[PDB]
Length: 52
Length: 50
Image (cartoon, rainbow over all chains, first blue to last red; front, side, top):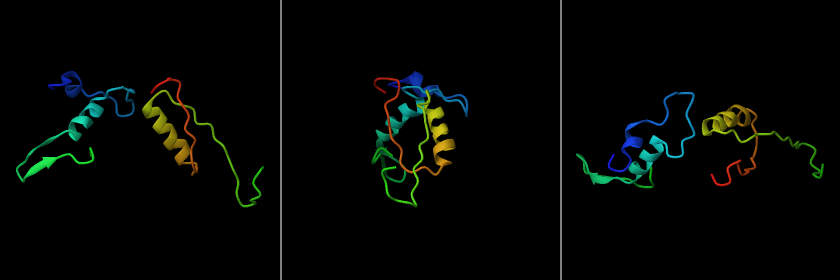
C-alpha cells in the first residue's frame, strides 16, 4: 500500500472464469512483495527464498 | 515423409494465440493436454513485445 495501494487493495480479477489479462495484476504485484519480505516472526525469523 | 520409421506417426494441430492468458491456458489445457501431444513450438504473439 506504500507502493501501489490501488493495485494492492483492489483485486484484479472479479470473475472465477473471466480474468482480464492485466499487465500488473493485483496478485502479480503482491507476488513481488511476497518475494521481498524479511522480518522477525513469533517462532523466529521469516524471509523469502527463491521468491517462492 | 522423410523419416523411415514405420511405428511413428506425426500430426500437427493449429493452436492460435488466444488474446488472453486465461483463454490461452484454457485452450491449451482443453486441446493440447487432451491430445497427449508431444513437444510444442513457440511463436511470437501479435504484440511486438509481450
